Amino acid sequence: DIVLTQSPASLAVSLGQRATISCKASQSVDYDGDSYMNWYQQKPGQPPKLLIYAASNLESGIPARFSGSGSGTDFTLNIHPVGEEDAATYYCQQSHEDPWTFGGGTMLEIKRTVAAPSVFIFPPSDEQLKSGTASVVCLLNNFYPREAKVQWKVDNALQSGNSQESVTEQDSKDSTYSLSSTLTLSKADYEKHKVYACEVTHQGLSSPVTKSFNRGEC
Amino acid sequence: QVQLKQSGTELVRPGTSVKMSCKAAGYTFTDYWIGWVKQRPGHGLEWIGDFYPGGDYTLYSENFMGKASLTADTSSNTAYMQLSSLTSEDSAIYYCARGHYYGYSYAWFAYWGQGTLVTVSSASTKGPSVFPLAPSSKGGTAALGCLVKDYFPEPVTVSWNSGALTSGVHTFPAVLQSSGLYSLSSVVTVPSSSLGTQTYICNVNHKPSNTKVDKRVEPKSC
Image (cartoon, rainbow over all chains, first blue to last red; front, side, top):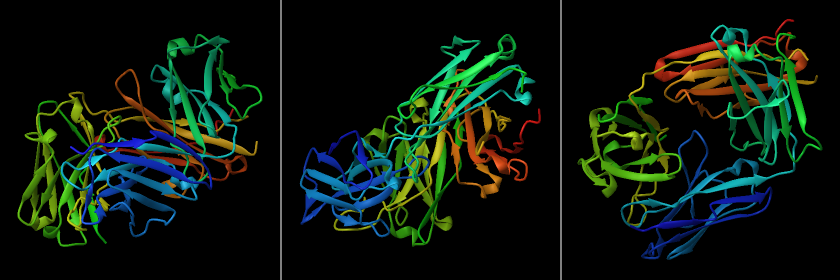
């Protein structure tokens, strides 16, 4: 098979600047003056989108901020100027001989200004408490960079092993992330404690932010 | 316009086969190869095989020999892929895509189906409960949402106000809980001044269970 090695695996590029992604093939993909290498963009929930075909041809409808170069075994995809909407994973793919093979992908992060999260806490709903389980949700909205620490405290005791986090893909309009953390307790354990707190640490915050509620106090 | 429309989400048992479809419109179906591609987290994109409906020609990856079978029904412009001897390694999103001739190849895939998600499992389908994430009683901007709990298999989709509210919405990737069931939250930030005058409804769809829930999220009056 023709093996394709992409580099880097992940790349962060400043808004407005140039992103360059490399793809190296284990054998030449040239024939009769054309280089049989393609580039795709993929965002979560969507199929891949063809950007560049035969190394340098811009697919109709794709912005000319995208360009491709190279021949033989060495190819590049260039994006300039980078915009918020370019956050995505990019793949090379060769069409020279079967099996058709893809590179491993490169995730592109768009580097924007630091933005602190806005933090919100949600108690379990009365509807859910009818069922014997309690989900407590902490939301961190529209922050950058991605690194963030969320710690749960119940009656000031730090929790471990009973929460799960989910982070959005980078936003295609403002280049921020958002994060949800869900603390799961049995109803029996939930009613044994009073203070439920989410503590958030992030580069954009001068000191950790804590959001909390007292069970039943509403 | 060239369009490829794939069949819906599948939940199928290990050891069996699954047959999914890709219906084409906007071009002469018998004149173009349809390629099939597998996407599984941690494994990028992997090509399975190609099918030419104008003659029933096949081309497979050696890794799918004896595993994938490609066919078509030209009377309905529909291509099919069957995957046999299913295991958890076959849980993935599967795409169809149309190739076109440029130079001396056709593997330039410009048009893609939306994908078919396949889960290989013997566990039963379970539609979710939907709970409100009510806007706090304690500013300029308030956050509210819906918690979609305890469903299987993926996926769930969420809209707000039937698609009229899109700004400020974040629908999070689902998490696989240790119960073996998925959960996800969808949130939106809105003007706190709108909480008494604007209605907020999350529209939750879990097609595998035909569970469709419209949940009104109101401020908690305490």
